[PDB]
Image (spheres, rainbow, N blue to C red):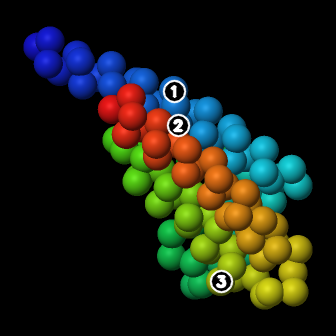
Amino acid sequence: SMEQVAMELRLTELTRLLRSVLDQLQDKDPARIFAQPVSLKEVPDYLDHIKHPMDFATMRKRLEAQGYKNLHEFEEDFDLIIDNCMKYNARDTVFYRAAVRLRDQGGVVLRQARREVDSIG
């Protein structure tokens, strides 16, 4: 149906906008702390601590399968990146501090992304 197609075109356009959001958020992580999944070879206990791991590569795979239906879904995954890191790592660590900075800087980007998603529809 044409209605199915139009819905598909909206998903595609949201996918475009979320790719640009993703790039901008990932630029706020120049150390690449959040670029890849935590390795279970190098942190064997990780899944005892963190039940839903997340990273920018895993978000990028979901994005390219058009797997985010709305901004809320995408933000949930972003927040997992930050929130997981801030539980596993102590306050005095470079990891925790990097999460804080990504959160604070990413807030700005997400604030305008929400306006654009609502505005364009």
Q: Is residue 80 above or below residue 96?
A: above
Say if mark 2 contacts mark 1, CB within 8 Å. Answer: yes
Image-based side of 47 in relation to 76, left or right: right
The amino acid on which the numbered mark 2 sits, given as a three-letter code, is: Leu
Kindly give the residue lying farthest to the left in the view shown: 1
Q: Residue at x 78, y 76 (%)?
A: 96
Residue kind at label 1, given as amino acid type = Arg
Tell me what residue is drawn at x 40 percent, y 24 percent.
Answer: 12
User: For numbered disc 3, what is the local secondary structure?
Assistant: helix
**Closer-to-camera residue (33/19):** 19
- Quarter of the image for residue 48 reads bottom right
Q: Which residue is mark 2?
A: 18
Name the residue nearer the viewer: 94 or 53. Answer: 94
Q: Which quadrant is home to the N terminus? A: top left
- Say left or right for 85 vs 5: right
Which residue matches tag 3?
87
Q: Residues within 10 Å of mark 1 (few under 14, many from 20)?
A: some
